[PDB]
Image (cartoon, coloured by chain):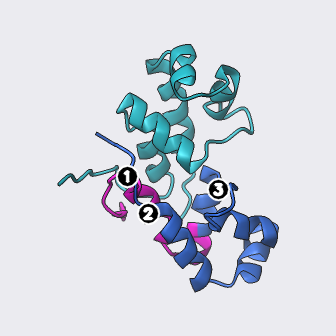
Chain colours: A cyan, B blue
Amino acid sequence: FQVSKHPHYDEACRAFAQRHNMAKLAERAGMNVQTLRNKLNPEQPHQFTPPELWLLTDLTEDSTLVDGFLAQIHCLPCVPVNE
Amino acid sequence: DFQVSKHPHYDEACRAFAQRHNMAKLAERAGMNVQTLRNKLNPEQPHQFTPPELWLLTDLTEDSTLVDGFLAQIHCLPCVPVNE
């Protein structure tokens, strides 16, 4: 695995802020709304933690953050499995 | 979908990753403090890796233990490379 040139995670972060209401999502996740914007802003040094990435993915049922996380290291998107 | 699992998948991967690799040698390659680097892999400590930190360590070690545990904590199969 090698880190890519194209910012796949940065484009996944900007797109995640596009779809969801940041005020409502930050409240449900118990996050300061400005800190959530910063961790989604590739212009700011704030970054998500693994527990934060799972929580936001769980509440929204959207894999944008995780899929962009995987493409940066050339992994295909999450393929879930149940049972 | 994408629900959080109650098993410590990412935690157990952090322990296995920490045991497999020398922490001092990885810290000087990754440009991190060796004590901070252990804290991220110690589940009993609240320190966590940032997304750039996980890509770098996966790059330097060519070991997908942390990424696969990251995927397993929310019910994703292990990483399948793109391979150009």
| Residues tagged 3 and 2 counted as in contact (Cβ below 8 A) | no
Tell me the residue at 71%/32% (across/down).
A43
What kind of element bears circle 1? Answer: loop
Read off the residue under disc 3. Answer: B49
Q: Which mark is residue A70?
A: none
Q: Residue A22 appears at what percent x and percent y?
A: 55, 18
Q: How far separated are the C-alphas under marks 2 and 1? A: 8 Å
Q: Nearer the viewer, residue B64 or B7?
A: B7
- Amino acid beneath label 2: His
Q: Residue B46 appears at what percent x and percent y?
A: 68, 55
Which is more foreground, mark 3 or mark 2?
2
Read off the residue under disc 2. Answer: B9
Q: Residue A13 appears at what percent x and percent y?
A: 54, 33
Q: Closer to the N terminus: mark 1 or mark 3?
A: 1
Badge 2: chain ID: B
Q: Quadrant of the C terminus of chain B?
A: bottom left
Crowding at label 3, few (<14), some or many (≥20) Cα neighbours within 10 Å?
Answer: some
Q: Which mark is residue B5?
A: 1
Tell me the residue at 38%/59% (across/down).
B72
Q: Residue B69 appears at what percent x and percent y?
A: 44, 63
Q: In the picture provided, is B48 more to the left or to the right than A51?
A: right
Crowding at label 2, few (<14), some or many (≥20) Cα neighbours within 10 Å?
Answer: some
Magenta-highlighted residues: B58-84
Q: Are marks 3 and 2 on the same chain?
A: yes
Q: Are marks 1 and 3 on the same chain?
A: yes
